[PDB]
Length: 98
Length: 264
Ligand SMILES: *[C@@H]1O[C@H](CO)[C@@H](O)[C@H](O)[C@H]1NC(C)=O
Ligand SMILES: *[C@@H]1O[C@H](CO)[C@@H](O)[C@H](O)[C@H]1NC(C)=O
Ligand SMILES: *[C@@H]1O[C@H](CO)[C@@H](O)[C@H](O)[C@H]1NC(C)=O
Ligand SMILES: [Cl-]
Image 1 (spheres, rainbow over the protein chains, first blue to last red):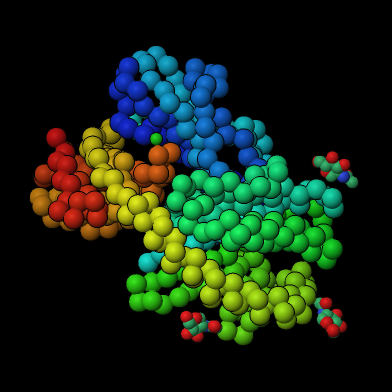
Image 2: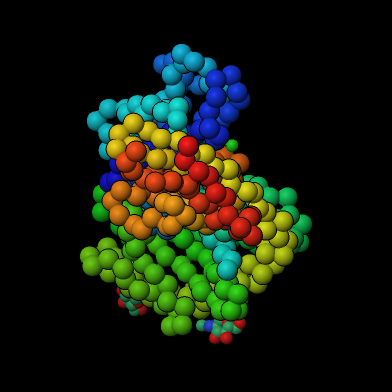
């Protein structure tokens, strides 16, 4: 099996009170079954949309999850990932610079 | 260069249960997919359906659905313990040359397992184990199917490709210019060039020190390209420096002329 490689990043350079999109991309994993949840202040973000599961030329699976958001000072954003390679769900915080 | 690619995958959970998915791609433009519950094909681009008559679509759908169904049946009939995953990647590529490349590969547990040989019209065993050896001999035995696969790959896939290049030319030729910012992270200082919004995917992001390209070393990381949801892409590149002038240079076909972003 292969553990997912996860990046969390926004569509545009973020700015407090300016509309944006938060992206969580999981890749390089096998088998394809995986949960990916975008989180805000410890709770699942509303409005999340899931790309079709796909795989790359070297057979590893990948998936893009995205939600519209307006980052505010004081909120925290993360992507939580469960996959059979992980003993527990892994929380990847959004670094608001990325 | 253009490519039409059909992707399929299947997790066999037990002897009676299999979760299938599939995707149709024209370069990185998603043409459609397989409804993992009903198995009906979904069409994502408006130029697709009118590009061929209904009867052609009917034959394409029925051949896709037979492929998927027969795949699952063959595996269950001839396999090795549950759970496991098979994948297929099937398609053709046209160079500007006019040169055709075809491909029809099956993977097993994420590694090449069987590969079609177009000229001989047979199968190459890709894993050095009994399961792959069995699969190769089984598929070697399907002479007639293999004759038909040859035509599907070399004639019908290519013909449909040429037609899709024309029908979907607006998608294929779509361009979106990159936007780039540069900022520094505490470290030595780590300079970051973050580029987003670009389409198509090929791009070249390099660092200049006094107008001069910084050579590769472990001080310079260029990251991996990341997708956005609106079919544009993002890249980050970094340079460990010591507090010379620095700028990030972004070259992209949407620009003809490059983006030059100084570090301040
Ligand atoms: C196969 O898998 C499904 C779903 O996980 C289950 O409902 C079904 O009864 C299984 N069959 C056997 C023989 O265990
Ligand atoms: C594939 O197609 C071209 C004609 O368009 C032909 O010249 C070439 O020999 C073909 N290869 C095979 C294996 O059929
Ligand atoms: C292929 O066919 C031969 C002869 O018709 C048969 O004896 C053999 O078992 C077949 N090979 C496989 C893997 O089915
Ligand atoms: Cl977006």
